[PDB]
Image (cartoon, rainbow, N blue to C red; front, side):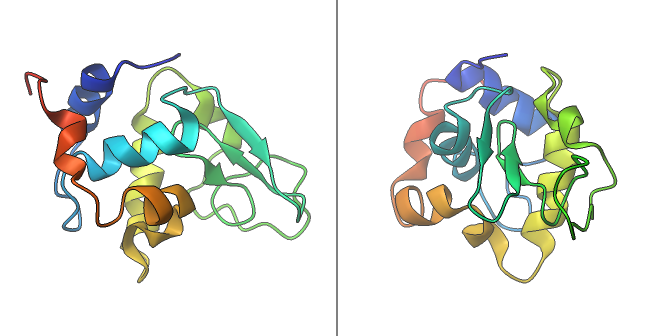
Length: 129
């Protein structure tokens, strides 16, 4: 599924991501925009052979099992395919584990290069939340 901007902001909000671990809603919508272009089915293969999955492009080397990343850790306890669902609950629960690691949202390279230090409030502007 491809989310609309305010539709995804509202879904992220209902699942407890606004201000989670100090990151306002809008950091999370900005990260999803540049990671997946709000598409839940987005996949991207990395040079090390691992693959990023879903709306928040969660990596198979540490966080999910895709059966083809030799050496992977599956810390969110879930097949990587569950992260491609139009229900974002799995991606939201795993993202919460990832931001809780000592790095915060710097784990997402597109948040670091194009959301971090920008007016991220713009991503939730006219939405009724």
